[PDB]
Amino acid sequence: KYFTTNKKGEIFELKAELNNEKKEKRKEAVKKVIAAMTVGKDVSSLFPDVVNCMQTDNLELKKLVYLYLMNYAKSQPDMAIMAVNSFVKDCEDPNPLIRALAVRTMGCIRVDKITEYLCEPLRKCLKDEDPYVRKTAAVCVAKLHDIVEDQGFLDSLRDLIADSNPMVVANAVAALSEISESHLLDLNPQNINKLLTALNECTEWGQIFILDCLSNYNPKDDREAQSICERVTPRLSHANSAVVLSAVKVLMKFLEDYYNMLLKKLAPPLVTLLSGEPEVQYVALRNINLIVQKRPEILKQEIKVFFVKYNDPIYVKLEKLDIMIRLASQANIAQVLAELKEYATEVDVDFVRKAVRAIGRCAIKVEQSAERCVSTLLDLIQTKVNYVVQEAIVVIRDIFRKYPNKYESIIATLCENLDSLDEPDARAAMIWIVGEYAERIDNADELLESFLEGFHDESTQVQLTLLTAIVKLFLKKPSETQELVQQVLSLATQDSDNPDLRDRGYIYWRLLSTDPVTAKEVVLSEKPLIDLIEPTLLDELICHIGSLASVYHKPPNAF
Amino acid sequence: MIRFILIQNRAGKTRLAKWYMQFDDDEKQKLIEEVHAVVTVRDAKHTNFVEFRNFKIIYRRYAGLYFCICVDVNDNNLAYLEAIHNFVEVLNEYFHNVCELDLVFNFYKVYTVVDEMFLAGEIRETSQTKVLKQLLMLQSL
Amino acid sequence: IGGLFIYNHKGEVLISRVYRDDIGRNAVDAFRVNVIHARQQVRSPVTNIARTSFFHVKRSNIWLAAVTKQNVNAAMVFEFLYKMCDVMAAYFGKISEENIKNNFVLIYELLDEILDFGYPQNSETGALKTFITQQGIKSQVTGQIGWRREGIKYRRNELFLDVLESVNLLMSPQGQVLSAHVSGRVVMKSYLSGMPECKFGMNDKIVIIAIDDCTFHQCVRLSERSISFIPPDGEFELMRYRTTKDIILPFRVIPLVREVGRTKLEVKVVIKSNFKPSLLAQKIEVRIPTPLNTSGVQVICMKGKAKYKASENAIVWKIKRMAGMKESQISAEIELLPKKWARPPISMNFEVPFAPSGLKVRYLKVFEPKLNYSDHDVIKWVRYIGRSGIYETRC
Amino acid sequence: RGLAVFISDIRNCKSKEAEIKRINKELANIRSKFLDGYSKKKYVCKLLFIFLLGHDIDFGHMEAVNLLSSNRYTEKQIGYLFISVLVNSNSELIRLINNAIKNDLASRNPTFMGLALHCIANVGSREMAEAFAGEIPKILVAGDTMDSVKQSAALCLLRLYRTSPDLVPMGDWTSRVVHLLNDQHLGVVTAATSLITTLAQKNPEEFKTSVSLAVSRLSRIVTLQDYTYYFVPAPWLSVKLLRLLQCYPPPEDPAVRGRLTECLETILNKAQEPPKSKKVQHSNAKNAVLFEAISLIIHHDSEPNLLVRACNQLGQFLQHRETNLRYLALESMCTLASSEFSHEAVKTHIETVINALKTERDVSVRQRAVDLLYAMCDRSNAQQIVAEMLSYLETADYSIREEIVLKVAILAEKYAVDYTWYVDTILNLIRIAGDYVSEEVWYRVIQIVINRDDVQGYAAKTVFEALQAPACHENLVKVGGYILGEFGNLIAGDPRSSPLIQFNLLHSKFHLCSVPTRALLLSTYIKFVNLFPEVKATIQDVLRSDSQLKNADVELQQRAVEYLRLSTV
Amino acid sequence: ESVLCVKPEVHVYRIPPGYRASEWQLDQPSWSGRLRITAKGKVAYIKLEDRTSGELFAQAPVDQFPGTAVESVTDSSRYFVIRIERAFIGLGFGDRGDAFDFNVALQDHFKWVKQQCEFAKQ
């Protein structure tokens, strides 16, 4: 009410030379209107004065008006409809850059009334003789569809597939594919042959669009599906990674001696995606993580490509590490453990903790290398690093559960590492190893007494494992540890206020006071010994190799 | 007490900044950019009272500009909202339906108005009649 | 592709263009809250929040976001976002907000001719000269090392890093963070034979009344987000920084203080450790101020211990350890001797084993040109020591 | 006219680097000129405008001080404006500036003294306090001083007291400052009240005679054509007079105290009246006096009749149109409810606050609504407040949800009437928002169920329907298993709550929950073996399944294997 | 063959003559182009390509990294003496971080070659 004048000011001074007669400094004016409203200045009062500059013959000045109009076409569409009479005069002008830019500007306006204006002037643009205009009109059908005469436009998209300029063919296929999400049949004789010949000549973004459409096609005969694949095979040599991953998605679908030759031609293009820029390697390695599950015989020999390089980002280091495990076999476990030992000495504390856990995943997967993984972790603990030692205790615990009564010489070396333990899960791993095997540990009660003095202010995982261990120590060594169990069950049932802790204290208190012989088969019995997408979801995500369903490893229903 | 007075548009660039507190030149730039990080976010139904780093900021927008006064936490925030509006009305008759560009071209006259009305972190003169009596007398001197 | 967003260094929208109205104006700030200002979230080039996917590529400052709602080819959008910025770099030189602000008109002419309803068109810079009318607005020998002596040898090469930083905070009793900044330094201890040249790498939480500031040691040469240097032998301050954005706050004090008349006072204070439970804060001391006319108080504590100190006029409450994602409470009952009480802030001391600015070390590659050792022969240690400075909550 | 050319020459730059070259070609031009005084002040306005854009200026100070010694007004006020903005610490310049100010202060031109008094009050360094702080009270005292100079001198002495209190000692001039409250020019009184207020913060008893002068002037102001501001008689002076009275206790003279009552009664009585204008600037100026009136009544805490009328006036602002009055009424009632006198009258507004909490959108006003509910809680209304907060938490946003859960659990234990209500309260709290409930809150709920027998049929019942929801919190599952495992027999008589249904209700949530949550549900599965022998076949296959025996956790395995051997042996 | 490292903006200095760096010209780069260290088998090839077409300006088989094929200059950490195949050629780099990746990728190759020899000695 105070700083709105319309007699003087910046809006007044802008409105002045926009009304002037020189063309070249009305062009400077509209640039000042775009640069005002980009930063966030309110130039809504200049709207009927900018569209007076539409009636001209200059191409540069007419685009600057259209750029001003496009910024209104999405946020406040009810204002940009007020100049729609100037659009429909421009969409039959010569200099067909004006005709295409008129049709784009009309299509981007979300107003129900504009469908009366994307009538009959649109169908001339679908039949235009400049292919740059047919390219524009092909997309604007999908703009109009996203808002029965347009059902007559749908067959005009099919007519544009038979064109000599292939970029017109490209956007028409991309238009039909988005329309077919909410409704195209690609029957062989003329559709597939004209798509694959346009595939060899169109631009790099249209080859994505054609190879995304062929994945919807269902072939019938086995050598008919083979006859497609000799044309798709040279498309996995392209510079773009989006073209290669779309070519793979067709070839992973149309996979019914040429079978053996095709799987040998999938491995060099998937290797060469990893020389790319780090966002692309993430998109590739999330798909490589799916391909080595469904077809593990493609990249069986290529584990050296997947070794983590130091300057990779953290989202490429963690995805390269999941594929090194899936290719970890007995023929190459020795160089994997050369790498996993090396990554565990890096300064990235987030990545070292996963490299040490990847060692125990190689011991569980490759059973023949269990001793080499145990000797690898022992060399890590001798470094005395705080975040490696207490990580490797967790991993050794899962080996003792997996391979019991084999590796228990090393506990005399693990038990001297107690003062380097401050994680709750890492302390609970040593208490389990002291709780088990206590007829092998010399001073198991002197170790477990050192934890009961600080029984509170420990985690309930540590409190429960220390409860389970001292009961196991009692049934293994009665009459030495009578003081510990009367200590810890007084700590559990009387001092602690956790209900889950104090009744587990009771269940042990009831069993020891009923029959310690009966408690031996209950507590100290032998425990039964103890990571891949299930093939319903897995075979779904191979049908979406390029897309975000494979980057997320989730079906498209959750998007 | 008042600690500064800001005038800045939605573009972010200031039209007046008078400081009543001893800050460094880069600290003055640091506060300015994080005032309109507060003021531009708030809508027309939020309150005009934002706590700001240990004191409070008081604003009102005049359709292209923000007048921000930054006072202590104890201060009467409903009286400093009207001393803002009292300061605009003095600028309204002194510049004859003031625009934004009167603050750009005549910044040295704006410091005369602020000294006339807000001196040493307090409100000096509230009367619109006596300020316009004083400012036009200095205009012809 | 629903809309290309180009954000500045600080997280503000420089220039943007939406192509699909499935994208709202909620999505321009959905990226700001949950990608740029992610406090503890580990970075990913594609993230998904609330049925909307976020593609971003950084070019040295600038967040180039790409927003979509469909199951689009993700390798398509990233290969687009490289050729979206190679078109711009061929017109601007580099990509920065000083070049983008000079070129709001050229980007708008590009963001229509390159991308059309989310469908990438021909991005060839030779073909664009027929379509783009506007023009871009353009804008030896180190001899001897002075700081490191020659012929150093050690029995075993080792290397120690300490990221040492201190949190400062003023927070309202409602939970609004009023002011926060972290002051830190990377102290490196180099026990390395020979004269190694080594490369250091970190994440992007450092900008290379507190103001965001970073100085280096004179050994460091800056020219990616990597740093090459030749470390002096021994104790050595590698980097020295302050930061103010996206501060990780380890604790929260919730001061529920009720005045009963003018003769009695009860104070409830709740501590919530706001970090992951595998970590463990230590040396925790919450001093709670009392009025000047306090007779004697009655304090009960859940864990830890507290004692009233009339010489300080404050209740000092000390906890030995606190695991993350937990909660403690103290209660107090003050009797007074009958103006109003001006409230000092509840100050707090602690020490956490993580770096509260978000700084992390990604790699540290040590290379000696003329000896028989390399990086995997070098034992490296990393330790994060978070600490409080002025960490206070209004009562 | 040369300035407006240069500014629009900067504004017509199309890049940042075009500015730097245009600035530097002008900085090189101005440096070459360093003249007519008109041509000298034009360049300083150029140099000042370059500074305010943020560019570094490292000259021009000696040219600006040469403007201070001029005799035309515009050359002086541009010279002082350069000095006030660009503060240099050259010891030669500070000597030259102080001599230029002593020339203007010794002058009897009121406009030349007005520039000098502002330049001291804008820079305010110690070197200007060391030369001037003995002259400024002499100008304020003297009877020949113009009233507009009396305004600027009083506020200039205010900053010299704020910057360096030791260089402004009190004395003879203090008894004549308080006489300015009797002055006819209200602008002089306005600059006087700000001066007396800050000086009475540390030496209150010296300025004690201003208490009687403040009330008598305020009684005339409340009960001036140039000082009305939208039909309100002198709002900012009446705000400053009410802040002056807050530096003191209620006065010694009961004739002063009685006069202080009806002026505060008049302010309250005007608030009840219909407004004399529709514009919001009338009501903001009208209420600016009112909230400082209420802050004075709270400060004294001496007339309970005024406190009751003040609380009744603040209840009118809770259901008000604008957000600015709803927020300030909630801050005031939090400070008002703590008093001995108004605390019973705030409690009558319990219906008004909750109806404001449910409908307010603004998150700042919404959380001061919660603080008022916590502040006015008592034994008499705790069941009402807690039940209304729980009715808010079912539809609340996640922004305010954390602090309300903390306040429900604090009011529940503190004001627990019996032990049947508290158990019903927190179990209702864990069902609604269980992820914000601390475990020592959750631990004590079970200790009351175990210790006392009467609630056990009621607690084990209410947990069972709480578990029938598809979206239970994981703390609800943990309190769900332990109570049904201990007291499922107390509700086994219901065919809707049959023992096989209680097991299937828990085991439907045994997955999709955490690792210590699964370990607690195993503990009650064996309690269903002990209590419910007809369920025993349906539990043991769950225990002997591979998902519990070959479970990757140690503690989930050790607890599942022991319970399979308790059930068979 | 695999490609170990690709570096643009790499200078080639003809050497006028030990091995100090200020002795060379350091202002007249005798050749400029793109650097690629390729390797196949047990050796590594330092191939110099022009920026535009990619023709092989020079090539140096290495076969041991601290050996005689690549020798560091004593003044700086950027300049290298290359035995192309014969003759000796002086390289150049822009900063340390380009010379860092030159030196690490060579050593990371011959670390792998030492391990594959050691696996054959098992």
Image: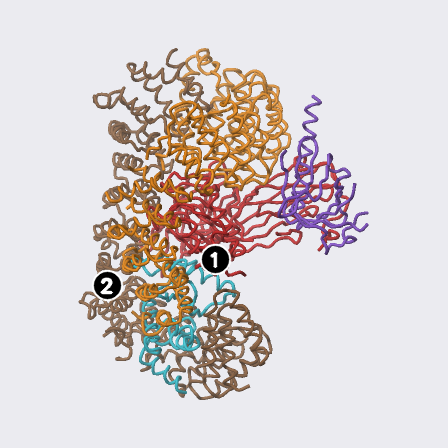
Relative vertical location of residue A386 with respect to residue D102 in this rendering, above or below: above
Q: Are marks 2 and 1 in contact (CB under 8 Å)?
A: no
Question: Which residue is label 2 attached to?
Answer: D306
Question: Which residue is label 1 attached to?
Answer: C100
Can you tell which mark lies on residue E58? none
Q: What quarter of the picture does the C terminus of chain A occupy? A: top left
Position of A369 with respect to B62 (left or right) is: right
Chain for disc number 2 = D
Where is residue A422 shown, x and y percent of the image? 54, 34
Q: Chain B appears what colour?
A: cyan
Q: Chain A appears what colour?
A: orange
Foreground of the two, A555 or E3: E3
Say few, some or many: other residues with alpha carbon within 10 Å of mark 2 (under 14 / 14 to 19 / 20 or more): many
Where is residue C133 shown, x and y percent of the image? 45, 59
Q: Chain C appears what colour?
A: red
Q: Chain D appears what colour?
A: brown
The structure residue drawn at horizontal position 26% and vertical position 42%, both measured from the top left corner, is A152
Say few, some or many: other residues with alpha carbon within 10 Å of mark 1 (under 14 / 14 to 19 / 20 or more): many
